Length: 51
Length: 302
Ligand SMILES: [Zn+2]
Image (cartoon, rainbow over all chains, first blue to last red; front, side, top):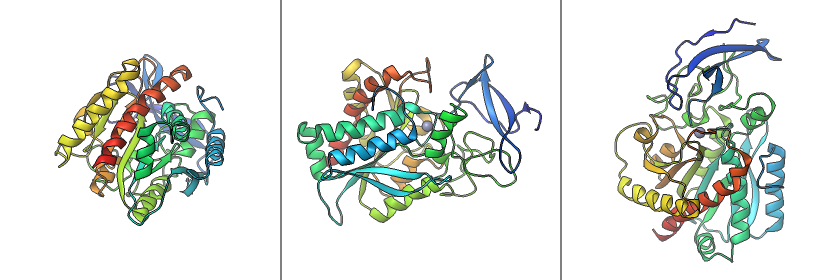
């Protein structure tokens, strides 16, 4: 599985403007063997950016 | 079926079946296509008649899966409509004039995913060639300044627009049905959160030709909504009231001849955000219903 790392082309996070973007991967049962996504955090807890 | 709790996709679908069974002359559950993973897209059609040009209103919910208050408000609304027909004169005359189509779960795959894997999942669950990131934002996928400012080219983004307009079968299904059926006069899209009632445009600062009327109608609806428990909403065009957003559903609706195009951002204002507790479902649904009726009364009267 790919190492988690800072996002590339993150964009804004309008609902939580100073949230942190991380590219986060987890092993999963698909063609790749894992699924990655952008995860945004504020004070170490996950948040959503758009409504 | 406890309308004051959140439910699985299967339970919501079953309750829609129960509603059409309770009121067969008024409500019918209709399949309009399927999701990426082959779950049915179900709408309820509420209708007292038929005509080649009979007007209709579309009520859209749950396009973004994590916005649980939207699907919950939608299923309660289905029950409210059949409960109040021929009792409340307002919804009765509305239904005597026009059809109401209601889609409580516009993104079924995402919804199941929020209950099995990731509570904050927003997008569809379609594949992205060459990428380990899954899904597109179904509310950036419509043919309304598609891929314009207000979306992302990155499959890993919350706001990925997809490879082309209507790529997402969930969206294509709604677009196809609305285009083929015709005569839609309203399109209302239920999201959360922020307590906003907005109208076009999201893709541009340009003023909608009907902006003055839509703003007036929206402010009336917000006042009706506040009458229940004092919940305050802001009103305005999407781009300047929340943020730029391209390829969104109401902009498509409005650019394709549907005049009364509105987005609701339901409760709350950030205390719970997307994780709104179940105990606010009924209060939210009741107040939202007064807002929806206000919009639909105006549709009826124009
Ligand atoms: Zn949304």
